[PDB]
């Protein structure tokens, strides 16, 4: 995982609603809502740096040559197809495995659709989601640039200008790095290429089957939805008062008897929001750690050749390839 | 409240604002009319038969009347009725003129003065233990007034009774008209009264010279519920017409609020009147005249942001409406430079065709800056200067020189 | 916090003990909550600071007290050394790196073929200036002449794809 | 927590249905906040 | 260090005890405890 969901909260709409009495009573705190929104804004701003650090390693969008001219290898499934979101085959497969800020007009949620869609019921209570600054197409273009630099220049494109070198003359280097001489590669090139192709084909066939394999990216979405729906449900709690509806309190009680009951709800819902923000602050840290690990793998495993054990895959490392998924990244490690 | 810039100034609590993009309050719509819908009732309530009767009941055999299909304009009591005690528990007295009541019952009886304090929840006396008791969740109103000129005679009135000598305390609203000899000791009783066997009823005296505390008082307890069911009873409020598809304040049978009223396909049952969504909020109601079903929808819905270059260089701004497709009405102003990005409708900035780096991030690949007369421009962000590599089949590039760099890292 | 004032001396100057305890309890609760929030936020920030401190302690060991081989860990380019400097509540590293400057193009082929036997460079790659054939290192063009000391032999010339023909000396 | 006691059996032995709610509510609020603090600090400890 | 101690909490037993009046009043919250136990269960599953 590389990122989570950004959110914003209008607290006057969640706590008080459209009543003016509650909104006048709520000025007596006035200092905690700005704090909550400060925290959430910090989170939201961190969530785009977490992506700029992973995917924007290079600032030269290298293009792919028309005729491959490779030694027998096949990157048709990882490289794009301009026909199509100019993604790749496996990337498309990935996006169709993880379910789920776009425009939702007031004319759509107007009617019975409201209170029945789970996204209109939030917006009607001050909770909104924000679109990320980098679109999926940009991320895929970055990934394609990285792939095309790896495939045509080895690792030199991560230490300065990009120098070109044939793919087999690069795998010979990557061989000498683990302890095997060159002749081993130049004398079994065809077989090695066939094995690589069959391995990637098995990858494609296992990802084209009906097993998820992407739970680490789905649990993020699930948690982020469960939190907001729990928050919406928490509005049916009385918190020690006679009712959870302000209009019922205001249709039967005067200005004096009603404050005793509205302050309870104010306090309760403010505490609810505090808890939400605390838990989000605690999860953002896990996401940041994972993003820093991914940014270290993109530089030690994609832009070079690692000598660390079990870091860039299980075995003697040869190379790795990146692919973009929803809220995260996938590495194919060749060992 | 003049504009979003002033709102963010008051938020940051400063008269200067640094450049960037800020989140503001959501788009609010204010009402224009007021709607009231009560049932169609013509007759008045029996205030006379109740408050101005000729014979009241006894506290042990108290009477309970029902009230239905009437209008409660208690102002008619201001002429000749004078109440010594009036206490409401689940409702305020200043709102009895704007509500409608569900299941109204009226309990009536007569006691002595110094027992009126016992008509309340949790009082532990002779009238609350053996004769008449009230729940602990009582919603209603208690009324009491002196009657020393009607219920008192010049030689003693012994037609009002109270129950002494019961074996166990009563329960809420439960009656008892049994007359069975009460046994004090453990020796048995066989319907005869002596030295341990007492008749469990006794009568007040109610003379006209007896002192306050021995003078008769008439009491009336009114019990009802509120805001859950049809409520055929209502107060003195004149209704209006029905305004659909507009933000209005409404009062449906005592339930207030503000929203947009729309037709529904839902079908209720003859014993239902409200909708009560997951969060216990109403999202449907039955009009008490046309008997049709109506939905209820809030008027406020949105999400609004403000783009600013800085209050020390310019005072022009741009505004982003996240839930509007201006390709147009849910806006504060219309301006003349609409763009309609994928993150919302941007109003206040001129769209260009070039591609620079991001200065102020907006969303979905769009950015904003202060370009050259100076204005605000919005554009699509750049990704880093497209390049290509010359991989033929058999060519290699080798360097012939180097450089020694020195970079910094702060931690 | 739902009380008549935020000053205890106005509460205690107008109200008795019983009426005032009701109002002081609310202030106590609210201020306690404020302090709890403060401490929670400081506990969450100390974690970030600790992670950064541990990373700096790792960089001191791997970049200053030694020469790292990881990519983009100490600098941008081929690492050489580093130097620390102290700053308020932090540290600053001056990373020294090697960066190639001037590229030149050549044609290349592996497994040179002298006479039925293939030869590989054993360190570096083969290049040609158009007519001649040299062997050189990878990150600094310094050509040498091809002998039997800077190469080794393996098998015969019937498999390799790209093999060329030239002379190797001794 | 601002109540007359910290024992529900000493409260429910003197006060009735309605006079006892205002105290049990305080105790509930306080003990719930205690549990919340415990869980928050354990969440912060588990990350180290 | 590699792990810590796993825990679980019964909120009705900590807050209300054996009383049946506090439980009915606590039902008016009913959803702040499940959150606690969800968090603690996450911790426990992570420690293994
Ligand atoms: C026949 C009973 C109808 C009950 C209707 C329901 C609620 C009405 C509530 C209170 C009515 C009595 C108010 C007393 C008048 C004010 C005191 C006075 O006189 O100065
Ligand atoms: C003689 C001293 C005994 C003290 C015993 C201790 C506590 C007793 C508490 C209250 C006793 C008061 C009796 C009031 C009778 C109910 C009112 C009535 O209907 O008349
Ligand atoms: C020259 C070349 O690229 N051939 C392969 C082709 O054999 C294979 O069937 C296809 C599957 O992805 O990809 C391509
Ligand atoms: C990559 C490859 O060619 N593997 C071959 C396999 O196809 C063949 O069936 C087997 C029989 O000798 O030997 C090995
Ligand atoms: C609370 C109350 O009044 N309960 C009475 C109880 O005294 C009596 O025993 C029962 C029948 O035996 O009828 C009922
Ligand atoms: C409610 C009531 O008045 N109680 C009656 C009483 O009048 C009558 O004397 C008795 C004998 O029939 O039955 C009972
Ligand atoms: C961002 C967005 O919502 N765009 C749609 C657009 O696709 C459509 O063509 C137009 C007319 O229906 O309404 C709007
Ligand atoms: C470093 C250098 O000069 N490389 C050139 C490249 O610019 C050119 O595009 C190519 C043509 O095939 O020949 C080589
Ligand atoms: C009840 O009777 C009195 C006569 O004493 C009368 O004046 C009064 O109008 C009656 N009450 C009402 C509400 O009319
Ligand atoms: C290498 O670069 C330096 C400047 O960085 C230059 O002065 C020198 O002439 C160059 N050497 C060659 C061989 O061109």
Image: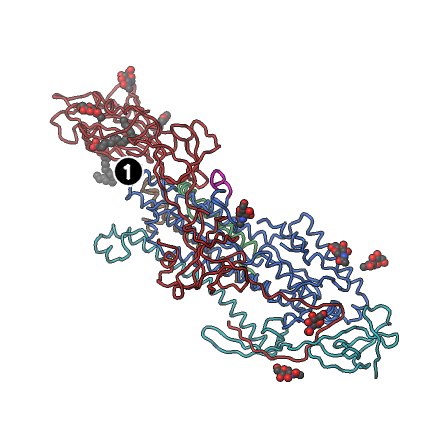
**Mark 1, other Cα within 10 Å: few <14 / some 14–19 / many ≥20:** some
Image side of residue E20 versus residue A51, left or right: left
* Foreground of the two, B395 or B226: B395
Query: What is the x, y in percent for residue A157?
Result: 65, 70
Residue at 76% across / 82% down in the picture? C144
**Nearest the eye: D11 or B136:** B136
The spot of residue C49 in percent (x, y) is 49, 67
Q: Is residue A114 magenta?
A: yes
Q: Is residue C142 above or below residue B243?
A: below
Closer-to-camera residue (A186/B173): A186
Specify the quarter for ligand 4.
Answer: bottom right
Q: Is residue B47 magenta?
A: no
Image-based side of B399 in relation to C89, left or right: right
Q: Quadrant of residue B169?
A: top left
Q: Colour of chain A?
A: blue
Residue D12 place in picture, x, y as percent: 35, 42
From the image, which quarter does the C terminus of chain C lie in? Answer: bottom right
**Secondary structure under the numbered disc 1 in the rendered image:** loop
Colour of chain B, in one word, is red
Q: Which residue is mark 1?
A: B92
Q: Looking at the image, is B249 positioned above or below residue A320?
A: above
Q: Which chain is brown?
A: D
- Colour of chain E, in one word, is green
**Is residue B130 something one can see in this rendering?**
no
Which image quadrant is residue A158 in? bottom right
The part of the chain drawn in magenta is A109-117
Rendering colour mode: by chain
* Residue reaching furthest to the front: B373
- Magenta part, dominant SS: loop
In the picture, one chain is cyan; tell me its letter: C
């Amino acid at each position: 995982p590389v990122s989570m969901t950004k959110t914003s909260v209008d607290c006057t709409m969640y706590i008080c609603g459209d009543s003016t009495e509650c909104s006048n009573l709520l000025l007596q705190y006035g200092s905690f809502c700005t704090q909550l929104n400060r925290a959430l804004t910090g989170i939201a701003v961190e969530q785009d740096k977490n992506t700029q650090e992973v995917f924007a390693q290079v600032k030269q969008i290298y293009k792919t040559p028309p005729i491959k001219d490779f030694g027998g290898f096949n990157f048709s499934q990882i490289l794009p197809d301009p026909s199509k979101s100019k993604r790749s085959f496996i990337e498309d497969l990935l996006f169709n495995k993880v379910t789920l800020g776009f425009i939702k007009q007031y004319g759509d949620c107007l009617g019975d659709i409201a209170a029945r869609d789970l996204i209109c019921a939030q917006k009607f209570n001050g909770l909104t989601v924000l679109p990320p600054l980098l679109t999926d197409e940009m991320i895929a273009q970055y990934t394609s640039a990285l792939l095309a630099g790896t495939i045509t220049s080895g690792w030199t494109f991560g230490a300065g200008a990009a120098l070109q070198i044939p793919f087999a003359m690069q795998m010979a280097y990557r061989f000498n790095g683990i302890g095997v001489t060159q002749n081993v590669l130049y004398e079994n090139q065809k077989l090695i290429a066939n094995q690589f192709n069959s391995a990637i084909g098995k990858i494609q066939d296992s990802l084209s089957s009906t097993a998820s394999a992407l739970g680490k990216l789905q649990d993020v979405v699930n948690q982020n939805a469960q939190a907001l729906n729990t928050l919406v449900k928490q509005l049916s709690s009385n918190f020690g008062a006679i009712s959870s509806v302000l209009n019922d309190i205001l249709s039967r009680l005067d200005k004096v008897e009603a404050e005793v009951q509205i302050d309870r709800l104010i306090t309760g819902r403010l505490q609810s929001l505090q808890t939400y923000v605390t838990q989000q602050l605690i999860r953002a840290a896990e996401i940041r750690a994972s993003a820093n690990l991914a940014a270290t793998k993109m530089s030690e495993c994609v832009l070079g050749q690692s000598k660390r054990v079990d870091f860039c895959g299980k075995g003697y490392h040869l190379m790795s390839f990146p692919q973009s998924a929803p809220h995260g990244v996938v590495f194919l490690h060749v060992t | 409240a003049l504009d979003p810039l002033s709102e963010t100034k008051c938020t940051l609590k400063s008269f200067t604002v640094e450049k960037g993009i800020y989140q503001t309050s959501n788009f609010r719509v204010q009402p224009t009319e007021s709607i009231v819908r009560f049932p169609n009732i013509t007759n008045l309530c029996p205030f006379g038969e109740v408050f101005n009767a000729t014979r009241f009941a006894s506290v042990y055999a108290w009477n309970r009347k029902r009230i239905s299909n009437c209008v409660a304009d208690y102002s008619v009591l201001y002429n000749s009725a004078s109440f010594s005690t009036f206490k409401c528990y689940g409702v305020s007295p200043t709102k009895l003129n704007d509500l409608c009541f569900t299941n109204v019952y009226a309990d009536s009886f007569v006691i002595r003065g110094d027992e009126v304090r016992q008509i309340a929840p949790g009082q532990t006396g002779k009238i609350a233990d053996y004769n008449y008791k009230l729940p602990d969740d009582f919603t209603g109103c208690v009324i009491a007034w002196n009657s020393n000129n009607l219920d008192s005679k010049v030689g003693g009135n012994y037609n009002y009774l109270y129950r002494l000598f019961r074996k166990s305390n009563l329960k809420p609203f439960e009656r008892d008209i049994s007359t069975e000899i009460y046994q004090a000791g453990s020796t048995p009783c066989n319907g005869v009264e002596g030295f341990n066997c007492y008749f469990p009823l006794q009568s007040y005296g109610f003379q006209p010279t007896n002192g306050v505390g021995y003078q008769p008082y008439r009491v009336v307890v009114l019990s009802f519920e509120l805001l859950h069911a049809p409520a055929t009873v209502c107060g003195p409020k004149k209704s209006t017409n029905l305004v659909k598809n507009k933000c209005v304040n409404f009062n449906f049978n005592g339930l207030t609020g503000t929203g947009v009223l729309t037709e529904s396909n839902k079908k209720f049952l003859p014993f239902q009147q409200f909708g009560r969504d997951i969060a216990d909020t109403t999202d449907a109601v039955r009009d008490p005249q046309t008997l049709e079903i109506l939905d209820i929808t809030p008027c406020s819905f949105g999400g609004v942001s403000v783009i600013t270059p800085g209050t020390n260089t310019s005072n022009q701004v741009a505004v982003l409406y996240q839930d509007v497709n201006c390709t147009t009405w849910r806006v504060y102003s219309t301006g003349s430079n609409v763009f309609q990005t994928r993150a919302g409708c941007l109003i206040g900035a001129e769209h260009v065709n070039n591609s620079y780096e991001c200065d102020i991030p907006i969303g979905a690949g769009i950015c904003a800056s202060y370009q050259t007369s100076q204005s605000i421009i919005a554009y699509t962000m750049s990704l880093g200067a497209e390049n290509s590599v010359a991989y033929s089949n058999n060519s290699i590039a080798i360097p012939t020189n180097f450089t020694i760099s020195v970079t910094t890292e702060i931690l | 916090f739902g009380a008549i004032s935020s000053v205890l001396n106005d509460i205690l100057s107008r109200l008795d003990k019983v009426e005032a305890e009701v109002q002081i309890d609310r202030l106590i609760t609210g201020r306690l909550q404020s302090l709890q929030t403060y401490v929670t936020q400081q506990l969450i920030r100390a974690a970030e600071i600790r992670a950064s401190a541990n990373l700096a302690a790792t960089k001191m060991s791997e970049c200053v007290l030694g020469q790292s081989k990881r990519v983009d860990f100490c600098g941008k380019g081929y690492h050489l050394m580093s130097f620390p400097q102290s700053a308020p509540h932090g540290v600053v590293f001056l990373h020294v790196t090697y960066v190639p400057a001037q590229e030149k193009n050549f044609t290349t082929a592996p497994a040179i073929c002298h006479d039925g036997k293939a030869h590989f460079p054993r360190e570096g790659v083969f290049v040609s200036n158009g007519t001649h054939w040299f062997v050189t290192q990878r990150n600094f063009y310094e050509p040498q002449i091809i002998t039997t000391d800077n190469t080794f032999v393996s098998g015969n010339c019937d498999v390799v794809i790209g093999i060329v023909n030239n002379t190797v000396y001794d």
